[PDB]
Image (cartoon, rainbow, N blue to C red; front, side, top):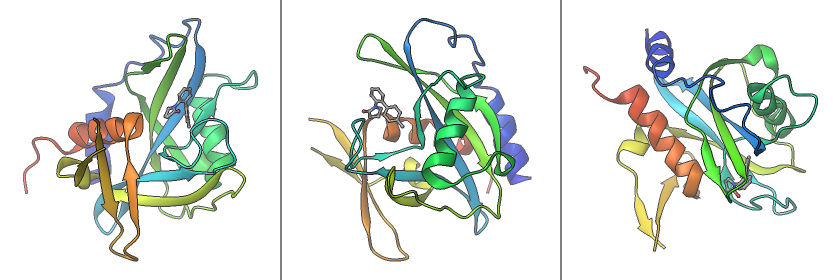
Length: 186
Ligand SMILES: Cc1ccc(-c2ccccc2N2CCCC2=O)cc1
C-alpha cells in the first residue's frame, strides 16, 4: 500500500541514534506526513512573530531538547503537541534522517512521522500563526524564486494563499519527496 511503501522507503535512510549523544545544543523537528485525497502531504507551521527562534518563518514543528525528553524523537513529539495539538497516539515516528549542523555548536535532528487520518490541527497561537499542508509531489517541481538563494513559493488552491518555504525546511521537504517518490510506477 501507499503508506507501507513510504515507511519501507524511509527506513532505508534511518541513521537512528548514531549522532544523538554528541555534545551539541540539541533541537529536533518532526516532518509530519499526512495522507489526503490519495496523496502524501507534509504539514508545515508558520511560527509566531513573538518567538526568539525563527519568528514568522515557515518551519516544521519542533524545538529545543529539555531534560524530560527520553530521546531526540521525544523532543519532536513534545513540541509538535505544544504547537499543533498532535497527541502521541496520533503519530508513528518512522525514522531519523540526517541531522543538520548549524552555528558550529548546534545539531538539529529531523524525524519523519506518519500522522493519523483523524488528526485535526489545533494551532496554538502562542507558538504558531498558521498550519498548512503541501503535497509531497510539489517538491519535485517547485516554483522557485531567487532572493542569492533559492526560495519555494506554494499557493494553496483552496484559498489562494501563498507561502514561502526556504532554508533547512525547504531542504528537508525535498529530501523526503525524493526518498518517498523517486522511481515509482504510475
Ligand atoms: C523548530 C525549530 C527547530 C530548530 C531551530 C533552530 C535552532 C537553532 C538554530 C537555528 C534554527 N533554525 C532552523 C530553521 C531556521 C532556524 O532558525 C528553529 C526552529
